[PDB]
Amino acid sequence: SVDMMDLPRSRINAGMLAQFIDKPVCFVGRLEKIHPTGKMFILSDGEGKNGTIELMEPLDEEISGIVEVVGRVTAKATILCTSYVQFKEDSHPFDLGLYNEAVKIIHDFPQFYPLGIV
Amino acid sequence: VDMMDLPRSRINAGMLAQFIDKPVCFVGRLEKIHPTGKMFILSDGEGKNGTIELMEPLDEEISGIVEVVGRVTAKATILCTSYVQFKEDSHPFDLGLYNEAVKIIHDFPQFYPLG
Amino acid sequence: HIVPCTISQLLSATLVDEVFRIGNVEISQVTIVGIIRHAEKAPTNIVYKIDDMTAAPMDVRQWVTVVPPETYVKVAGHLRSFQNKKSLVAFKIMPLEDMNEFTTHILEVINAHMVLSK
Amino acid sequence: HIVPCTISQLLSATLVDEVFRIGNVEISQVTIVGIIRHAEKAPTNIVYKIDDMTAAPMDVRQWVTVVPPETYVKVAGHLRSFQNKKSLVAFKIMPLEDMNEFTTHILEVINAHMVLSKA
């Protein structure tokens, strides 16, 4: 498939998933649960709403805490994950609520936080 | 009775139903004047209409961008207590941008407090 | 720096140690945008009642021309309190020529306070 | 001063007579925050590929300990261009200890560019 790392990816929350079907996204949330197959997991955003993350292959490590997923929103309004990283929280807890307000700001003031070229 | 003494919420037509009996400030483009001159229609920044009922008939024509202060009625119209035409002689008023500001106001109540 | 505010925000400022704060945001020099409801030319000063719709009109004073009522103006000045009654001592009261500057002020308030709040 | 930017904003800059602008505003010194996707080490310098999600990752050269990929950093540097490809030359590359500084940068970007848009 196309390389998503070379496209703009929109920072969204779970309430935006339905509006972003088939779009490259970046979803930051708290790990809530990993499916027994290790091929799916749930993240909750800074509003406490859940998003479902799917993988093509099983997780090869135990993830926890705040996780940032990049992928494409599927027809089901899940995210097909092409990559992810766990946010470092060993010196400061990540304020996911503040992050949510920043996501809202990004979308309300798009002229000042452009998605891709101009 | 004196509404100048309470907060009036800046809204667009889509919020009228959610603000029944509340003091509001509605900015929009003059679309139509009722033949009695005792009511007019404003269109907001997303092309939706709000109906403005006046207590007294208009004296002069009004046109262009109008800011109405009033209370929302049970019919989701506005009973107007005052209105002013926005000056636009130097620069055209961008009603679409204004509508964006109304959405933002309501998205961030903590940073634009009513009371 | 100078901070864009609403009158509701100024009215809600706390005074403690002679620093004013709107939330955690310390403020002194501020701007507001409003319509002149009442203009009072006294021999020793002008006093304006300025209304931004977010609360009752606020007292804005200049020490001694007078701006007519129903005029949207931009105001720059300093927050003053006496017996917990707030008021504005203004070094600038400028009628708006471009009404878009009024819309812009709303955006500026919300943005400044977002970024300043922490 | 030093302007906080997104990579998308940097890409959008026009270059006219040795001068970059976003609008009518000269920019040279900037900060970005992003994740390292790649690091290419040479004796005298490192080139990082840094991704802030706003666009494709941008090259950032630091003149010389390499920051490991998948690390979030703040970069202070100057915008440069060659054959119409923009990149940064960094005087600071700082891994973030507190991930809230990443969130804060988003807000600083938006505020800075609002303010500059009126000037």
Image (spheres, coloured by chain):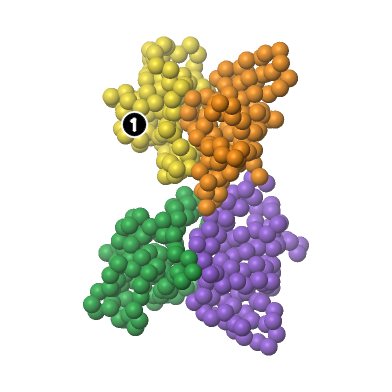
Chain colours: A green, B yellow, C orange, D purple
Chain ID, mark 1: B
Task: Compare residues B42 and C91 and report the one nearer the observer.
Answer: C91
Give the quadrant of residue A29.
Answer: bottom left
- Residue pictured at 53% horizontal, 62% vertical: D101
Q: Position of residue C50 (x, y in %)?
A: 56, 25
- Name the residue at 52% across, 24% down: C57
In screen coordinates, is D10 left or right of B53?
right
Give the x, y percent position of residue A4: 44, 72
Q: Is residue B90 above or below residue D97?
A: above
How crowded pointer 1 is (Cα within 10 Å; few <14, some 14-19, many 20+) is rated as some
Q: What residue would you read off at disc 1?
A: B19
Residue D96 is at least partly visible in this image: yes
The tally of labels here is: 1
Which corner quadrant of the image does residue D93 belong to? bottom right
Three-letter amino acid code at disc 1? Phe
Q: Nearer the viewer, residue B88 or B56?
A: B56
Furthest toward the left, the residue is: A36
- The reply, left or right, for residue D100 in relation to residue D29 is left
Q: Residue at x 57, y 56 (%)?
A: D109
Query: Residue D15: in sight, yes or no?
Result: no
Q: Considering only vertical position in the picture, is D116 above or below A2?
A: above
| Up/down of C61 relative to B56, above or below | below
Q: Where is residue A66? Give x, y as percent.
A: 40, 68
Image side of residue B105 versus residue C63, left or right: left
Q: Position of residue D27 (x, y in %)?
A: 69, 59
Nearer-the-camera pick, C44 or A47: C44
Please tell me which residue is depicted at 49% across the width and 72% down the height of the picture.
A6
